[PDB]
Amino acid sequence: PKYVKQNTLKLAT
Amino acid sequence: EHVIIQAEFYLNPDQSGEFMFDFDGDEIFHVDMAKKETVWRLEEFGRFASFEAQGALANIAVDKANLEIMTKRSNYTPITNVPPEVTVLTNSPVELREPNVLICFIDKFTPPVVNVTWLRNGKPVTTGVSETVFLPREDHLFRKFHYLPFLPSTEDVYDCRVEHWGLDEPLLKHWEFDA
Amino acid sequence: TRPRFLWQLKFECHFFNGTERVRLLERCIYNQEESVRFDSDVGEYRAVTELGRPDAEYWNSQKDLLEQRRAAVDTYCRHNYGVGESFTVQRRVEPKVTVYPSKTQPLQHHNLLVCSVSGFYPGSIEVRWFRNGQEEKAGVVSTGLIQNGDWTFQTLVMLETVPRSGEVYTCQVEHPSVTSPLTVEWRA
Amino acid sequence: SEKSEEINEKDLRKKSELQGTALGNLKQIYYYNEKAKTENKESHDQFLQHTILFKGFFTDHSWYNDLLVDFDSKDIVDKYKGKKVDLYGAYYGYQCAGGTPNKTACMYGGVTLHDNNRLTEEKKVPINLWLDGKQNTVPLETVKTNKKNVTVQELDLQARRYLQEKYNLYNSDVFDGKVQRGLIVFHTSTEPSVNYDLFGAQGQYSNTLLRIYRDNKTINSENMHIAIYLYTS
């Protein structure tokens, strides 16, 4: 059972 | 009923960051940024599940990136110091000549940078002392832990030394068996 | 020393009734102010303070990214939930109950009693007192749920009284780790 | 140096023991691959605290533009952060993160101090090799270095390029690579000697294949010499 992370996004430049 | 939290952070100028998972307030696991390996709270958790540490390392790269942005757009306004609350405690009702463990619960504090040191009769210690990464709270401050094992006595007096940037002077917390 | 700047990021999974109800709540916080967040119950990003503005309008633009952040309820929240179900949700350790007096005194000069449950998990716990089989909701001052961080709890429910000989006090504790409430009695 | 019937003893790993594309990556890292080497650089730029990033370090590269150096500790970073520095290591791409997204490469150590580190004259590092105890004559130009305190990495990346050119060290047994084992001692007089099993590399990718250089070891160049023992057994 693999834990899946949640990718962080880049803010508004 | 239950809540999992993928909480993480990056702090400047400390250039330090962290990534860990949380189940109802109890760290499930965190990534050791440096060793680039997932560290299960209770060794048990690992004989069951997993976590590609490599992933956290990358998320944080972005966080760093987002902080730079925000710090700029916020026009370099800095975090306001918030002094923690320490509360020395024990694992179970101390029994003379019966093992125990002194807990040092640092709480309600930010930014995530706090020094802790264990004093036995004034002196420092390394008797199986470990800690916990910065745990999250609903108000976004942090809650931390520090444990020190010890065989009770009357021949001893202990203390939790906690240094933070919201404090005007180190914070001492004494603990001693009462008879 | 120097100023500090911080960025906190939280991805929250509120599980109601096991898995029958889930709510993902992605939260962006700068220093200690949440600037932008996503909510499964709303489906898109939304600012919560002026600084959030750029962000919100942004992300919601990529209907492609949004579509993902909406399914994340099944690939992330739900998926993760059952990954650790066994050692977290199912996690169960029977408490250790003990009774003792605080400041040994000369009987009948009003005292205090402290039950010290210790060893816990889950937290949801109960501990009533019973002087001679009679429950008391009067004089049971409690410290509250104390979390130790090693996945174990320990509460201390105290009771103030006056030790009349013969009286038999008792601390009862129901826990989901035990089919029958545990007990411990103390002679006055 | 030492006896080749005694160094012949220590428990070196074998080429037998190499799982998957690993081997091809040692021949990748050491022979074909490119590597950093650029004097007088600076920075107090990082990713996490055990690292140092060289913002805009690569100029005219089709993918990267940043190289992030990985050290063992902040401690080690404080010796080199914001100071004049020289690099000389083997970098990489797969997995790496911290620099300009997707355009960043990682390294491990290979960093020396700049100020007062140049030698009066280029130092040719004397190498003693052994191909089954039978010493062989390996040219003086083989391992050069202008630094006084050279990093163990800078010397090795070189010798490891000779053993390929001369003995096909990392080529499979098929593509004729007789050597099944081999060691390498960096011989210094006034300090402890550095020992590196030639096939005791852990992992399959560069990310682990380069860890050996993470302590960023730096020895005194002069009076020194190299020693190599290879085994076909």
Image (spheres, coloured by chain):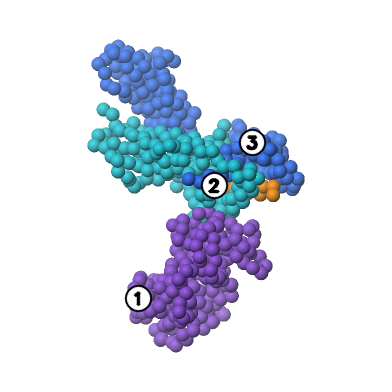
**Separation (CA) of disc 2 from disc 3:** 31 Å
Position of residue B16 relative to residue C50, above or below, is: below
Q: Which mark is residue C22?
A: 3
Chain where mark 3 sits: C
The chain painted purple is: D
Q: Amino acid at mark 3?
A: Val
**Circle 2 chain:** B
Visual hue assigned to chain A = orange
Occupied quadrant, residue D12: bottom left
The amino acid type, in three-letter code, at marker 2 is Leu
Pointer 2 with pointer 1, Cβ within 8 A? no
Viewer-nearest residue: D81 or D154: D81
Q: Where is residue D185 drawn, in percent x and y? A: 40, 75
Going by the image, does D143 lie left or right of C33?
left
What colour has chain C? blue
- Residue where numbered disc 1 is placed: D189
Position of residue C89 relative to residue D161, above or below, is above
The quarter of the picture where the C terminus of chain C appears is top left
| Residue that appears at 62% across and 63% down | D56
